[PDB]
Image 1 (cartoon, rainbow over the protein chains, first blue to last red):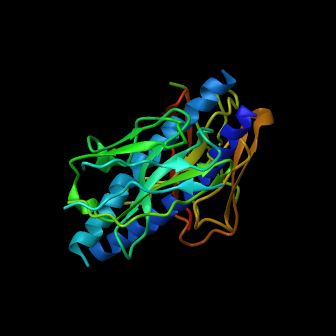
Image 2: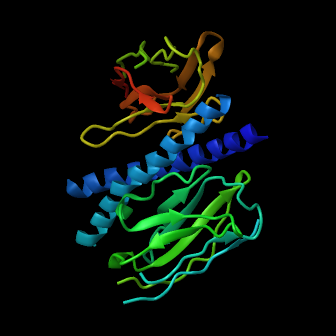
Length: 36
Length: 36
Length: 111
Length: 112
């Protein structure tokens, strides 16, 4: 059971991070565009 | 030990974002403070 | 699941924050704090997990700190002699039992 | 330090893979991923994957970037198709053993 909870929260957090990281990829390239 | 290193994952993980979006939030704040 | 959100306040700190769950007590998954300057996108503030790991969002080192008991899952977080610009809605926000969950969020002046 | 070498890329205009095997912890599957970094900016990730089958992706590369694995000889898969002319991007695995993160030679795979 314990392993189950650890596992599930792992998958959720990688979901979260991937979305957040794509978003700021977009934001940083936007910052660079307004730089140029 | 199956716990010990599986559990050893999250703390670096939760440390990753916490450092990560900091500048990413700081920069987009610094996007907002001086652009719009 | 059900949660509880309160404890923020309105200042210019000397106040307490108390963040609990109505259930799922202390099954301590990853669980987080949030804030948002209005008209914008809400985000990360502070997070504690199975270990109460000592990390938050960079803008904290020396200003926002965790402190927990499972009393009613009423985890806390330390918000003293503040920094103003955070003046916005704060919200602890926890993710439990394979699913995320959201609190109320309260308008808060800090300055 | 564990030499996590990856290799086998190509430089042209699509299962191209920094052949992402192991010399330690042969699929000592704890935590691993790939990263990327677009020139003139910081680093990032194309896809973050997990030993637990939950191998999700960076929000954009959907429809073209999928990750799978072959642990039976420790061979995780960077499989692509139909190169989007933007796809000049850096490709390299990343891993976290004993908590310590790990990196290789990596590559800015020159592909359209």
